[PDB]
Amino acid sequence: VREPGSQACLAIDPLVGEEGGAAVAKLEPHLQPRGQPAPQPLHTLVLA
Amino acid sequence: AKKEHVPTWLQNTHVYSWPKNKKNILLRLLREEEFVAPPRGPLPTLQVVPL
């Protein structure tokens, strides 16, 4: 018999990087507020 | 989720659970073995002791 003291089985464990460094982000467009004096279309009429 | 929610054909392989098994998922994606066996040795020489 030859004992396994020198050739033991090996478990593997990845060195996981963490999301703290970077993460997914969502973009939000700043709609030009119409509460602020934003423009508006004008309909032209004729006083005949 | 629960085990019943796995489609049957997918129940014939390893089913990982997130986030519990995320390291195992990484190992699967890396296509590496979680347990590595040592190289197979030679068959043991048979010793004889007479009576």
Image: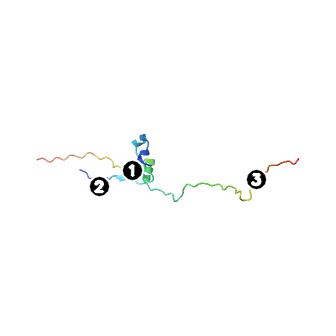
Same chain check for tags 3 and 2: yes
Mark 1 crowd level (few <14, some 14–19, many ≥20, 10 Å Cα): some
Disc 1 residue type (three-letter): Glu
Chain letter of mark 2 equals: A
In this view, the residue in front, B16 or B45, is B16
- Secondary structure at badge 1 equals loop
* Residues at marks 3 and 1, CA–CA distance in whole angstroms: 65 Å
Task: Kindly report which numbered mark, 2 or 1, lies closer to the viewer in this rendering.
Answer: 1
From this viewpoint, which residue is outermost toward the front?
A: A48
SS at circle 3: loop
Q: Residue at x 30, y 54 (%)?
A: A6
Q: Is residue B15 visible?
A: no
Residue sitting farthest toward the right = A48
First in sequence: mark 3 vs mark 2? 2
Q: CA distance from mark 3 to mark 2?
A: 83 Å
Specify the quadrant of the image occupied by residue A36.
bottom right
Name the residue beneath numbered marker 3: A40
Q: Is residue B21 left or right of residue B42?
A: right
Residue at numbered disc 1:
B34
The residue where tag 2 is placed is A5
